[PDB]
Length: 508
Image 1: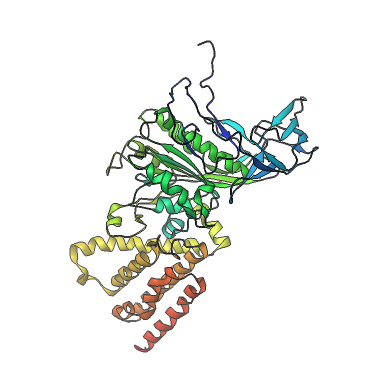
Image 2: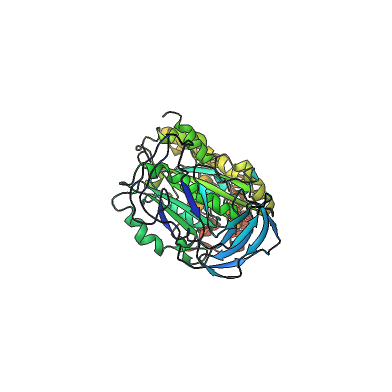
């Protein structure tokens, strides 16, 4: 073993035709054959990765004379109907642009540019580039969690935010119908690009993909969702070596898009031991370490991100070890899908007592500045509400509802509303399949004002049975189905008037 270095350098190729592509853990097209891993390097057999014959339209964005550093965008190629693919000087390369393509059509092998480094080396630049998957793509700076990744799902966006660049986790195997939140996240999050790692996929869980996935429309555009997605399959008779590798391959394609200025979401998908602890906590850590929002390389000042959502399919129902206990230490957000919520058909079945996100403080300020100054104070009060509900329910189990004073009945009432009116969301409703930021905070105020007003009326000796059947209530329940946000907002003044009436009819 004369040679050295730990690896052959498992490169990935990064250029046009990533999107719509379906690869495996090392980057070869659909329906492919067998590799081998280890301490040392690895071997292969055959495959290509981005077409060498496909002709791509290249628009130059720089003239001969321009000084460039690694990361600068020298050209643009429209890849799909959605993504403009941005062509960057590979990292490590700075100089004078001495020669540059004229707007036209080229294959990826062509030299679109040439750069004179300061030693004097002319360096040849094509529309694609290579990177060692095991090595984190560099950037200028890694910014603090700060901008939320807007999911359009109320419980997530309000109670358990994901930061752009953050890391979340989520139970079970992705491609299954006990949850569709997985899918919902992938299509609604305001990332531009999605990197999916479908993983361990079984028996006809690959046929779920190749058949349906290219038929999926992207709700923001009505174009294939695939046209802003890279797909990375981890099936059963593939080697352990192309599974261990995959997340790295994936996160690297991820880094490549954020380097463009994109926000990308990356979704991973363990199954019954995603490969076959020890120090293997580090191997996972350093995967998740590679998530982040960054000032990208470039001479312009450009921010991109890779936020990671990781699915946690355990050995089963136990959710205690191995992969499960370790992953939760690393991640900053857990959305706990709870089969008992699912059985009561409370969807999304995210348990509000046991999920958690450490990015609330991080993101409150985006919410306050751009959407509502009252955001954080509100989610807080809502949660306090729901926490109280949790406790009263324990007791009411033991002693029944008759024991309860009005005040308490008022709280179970409003909690209940909070649960059915806000936490519950209709993934299948044409309006409620997505709840924009401005809508979440309005709905929130409506409920919380109802609450404010409920207690007050109670403190004023109004019967709760009166409030319970107050008309505005039934409208509040339907709220989520209203697309016109200010029709929703009017429920506040409406709640007020109905309540005023109720003070009158009891006078005092």
